[PDB]
Image (tube, coloured by chain):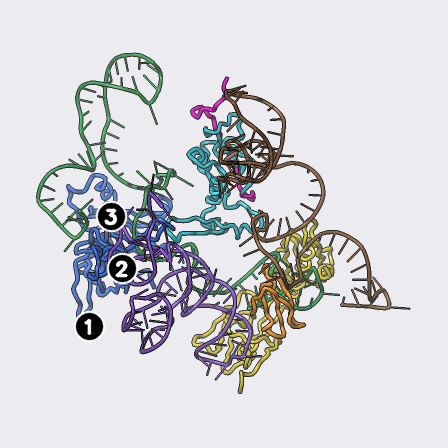
Chain colours: A yellow, B blue, C orange, D cyan, E green, F purple, G brown
Amino acid sequence: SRVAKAPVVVPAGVDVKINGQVITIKGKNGELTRTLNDAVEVKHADNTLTFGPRDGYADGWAQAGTARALLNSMVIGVTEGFTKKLQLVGVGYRAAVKGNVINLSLGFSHPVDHQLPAGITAECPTQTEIVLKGADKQVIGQVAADLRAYRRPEPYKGKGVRYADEVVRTKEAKKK
Amino acid sequence: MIGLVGKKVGMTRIFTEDGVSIPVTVIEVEANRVTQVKDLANDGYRAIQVTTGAKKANRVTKPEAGHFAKAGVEAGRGLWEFRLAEGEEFTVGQSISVELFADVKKVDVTGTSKGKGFAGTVKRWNFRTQDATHGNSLSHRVPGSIGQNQTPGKVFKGKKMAGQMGNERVTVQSLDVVRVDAERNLLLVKGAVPGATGSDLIVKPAVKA
Amino acid sequence: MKVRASVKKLCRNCKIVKRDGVIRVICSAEPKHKQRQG
Amino acid sequence: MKTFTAKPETVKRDWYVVDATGKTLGRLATELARRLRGKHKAEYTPHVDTGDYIIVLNADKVAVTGNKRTDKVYYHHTGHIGGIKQATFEEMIARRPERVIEIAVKGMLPKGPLGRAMFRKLKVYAGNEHNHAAQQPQVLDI
RNA sequence: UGCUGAAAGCAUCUAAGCACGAAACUUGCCCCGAGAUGAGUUCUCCCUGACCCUUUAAGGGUCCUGAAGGAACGUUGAAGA
RNA sequence: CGAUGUCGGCUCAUCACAUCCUGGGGCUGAAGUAGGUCCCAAGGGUAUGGCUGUUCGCCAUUUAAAGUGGUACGCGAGCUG
RNA sequence: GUGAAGAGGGAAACAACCCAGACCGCCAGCUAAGGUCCCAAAGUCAUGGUUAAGUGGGAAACGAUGUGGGAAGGCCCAGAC
């Protein structure tokens, strides 16, 4: 509605291909392709991207909004890219990158080795930071959710793999 | 991989050097020789049919003799079939020896067990005997009750009752192969395998991890 | 969480969401306010 | 005079091939059941199999509406006691989709020796080709 | 439990899309199993004669042949009422 | 009512889940260990004895646990009495 | 009122419910209740809505930004949410 009505301003050097419902967007950061719902009609009109509800379908407005935001993310994903930043709070928590495998030492009796998918590149400026970068937004959201999911932030102390921006609310023990 | 067809020679023991007796079963595995190879393009599945031993010339029938004659092989005492494992390749008339188990470390042995005939439910299903005294009237080894009452008013399927125990295919899994002797054509596995002495076995590599 | 047949907003941060045909109360302030099945 | 009765020695019956891609299961099934009874022929007779041979193909591509792709459950009991065995629609399409069309049509056909003989005339395939090119099935667009 | 994400310019695990997730479920393991009348497949083996009759049919009969194989019989079995 | 044998024990089960154990999980007045409570889950498992005709119960000593019910308060053309 | 002492059609099956009261015959028509996609006779009829829960095709207090309609009302492009 109010989201679908605002157009996606496509910057220079970004390639947009509308093959029916399939949308391919390729810029400086990588080819990234979706297939929208059938209730979304997308029109380029030479300057921007415009999203409207395909006629005959009930919830198409709602669908259109999603398509909007998704392609907005895709435009950032071919221009600037997305970056999640995770930090590891705990005594003896280690993070390293061999190739695209994130080795993690999280107080386990076995090493943790997370295989990143194809499009995502992680770095470690410190032993207790993982700054991972990529193009698709749900994919780095996914991967940061997995790395958090190995050791989630424990509530009493804060020990775990937290996001750099997220606040972790603590509490004391029962008595004394 | 594939297996080989043996013959239960009997049991012995193998004293180790540090003095631990190992109960072994001796399985003579002669030259299993391939009589047919089966491909997807003709049968829908990849498998070899082997034979072993030797049969009398007058006792093998003309169908059977024509089969072994096509294969270019001596008639054996039977035909068995092993499913192939996607990268294996055999030719017809190729002989397979116990040497195949020179790496395998643990096998599964399949035979027909010893036929115990019509067995009652105490032997067969380990039912527990009722009182041997204290009043009991002609019902010592009998099965007890066999079902409920008006609801269901039927005995359910696969109620454990008495009947033929024994004389059926059983596979013993994960037996430690103690020796492979290519000279005498022998395979010594640790433990008991199914069957009386002289019974035909089928020794495959263990599918369990 | 609390499976009840009356789910309500206990706090001002509590929030009614229907997921998979199930009414739920998702709070951010207090996780004791998490509820299901209204 | 007497009402005409079809004679099963002299019933002529044709071969039809039906593509089941994207058809609704019950609506296709009901049309097939009508054609296999022989209800579409004026020589219909309730104790004579007068229907046609139908070759249904692309049985794995049949469609259902709503959440019936995952909620429609096919129960059967095995005879052994706790033998109630269920399988949803997508599990059946994965394992054997022929069973989906054949269960439907079979439940729409009269139970009895005749309706078993009527179901023997339905030939379902999960693919696009059939062995029955010798019988020359003409394309029944339904 | 999430990720992206609107309807609801925020928020939101769900409406479109996507990822995890248990001894339950389908397989994997063992056994039975083509009467699976939907009675399947593969390999091999055997049989390559004449002549009548009629209400001419996948009809009946006579002579000559009797295969592959099975069954019977016997000696029997760690198979078996 | 021209008969449907009725407690308890034994033998033999079988289903339900409103789960005792094992398995997954949320909240905790959850530091850990051990818990409490609630959701999911029926695969498999789920005592021996003293007393008593007893089911039950109390006690002794175990156990991962000694589940709750239906099945003519399952089971006497199966046993006991 | 029906059954008893009343058949027939319907309600799956169902004395007592709905329709209807069987003298006999007919391979004739029209109807009642009830129905018309297939089992199973007859609309996969026409027009306009509603629900997506297989609701329809059990079950309440109570809970809930499910969704269609109606009448008002507060604030609002001196810019509201």
- Within the magenta stretch, is there residue B89? no
Residue placed under numbered mark 2 in the picture: B172
Respond whether the residues carrying marks 1 and 3 are from the same subunit: yes
Q: Position of residue G47 (x, y in %)?
A: 71, 39
Q: How many marks?
A: 3
Q: Position of residue E46 (x, y in %)?
A: 22, 33
Q: Chain of mark 2?
A: B
* Residue at screen point 53% across, 83% down: A174
Respond whether the residues carrying marks 1 and 2 are from the same subunit: yes
* Residue at screen point 48% across, 37% down: D109
Residue placed under numbered mark 1 in the picture: B20
Q: Up-down: is A40 above or below G64?
A: above
Mark sitting earlier along the chain (1/3): 1
Q: Can residue A65 be seen at all in this image of the molecule?
A: yes
User: Disc 2 residue type?
Assistant: Val
Residue placed under numbered mark 3 in the picture: B79
Q: Chain of mark 1?
A: B
Q: Which residues are magenta?
A: D1-25
SS category of the residue bearing label 2 = strand
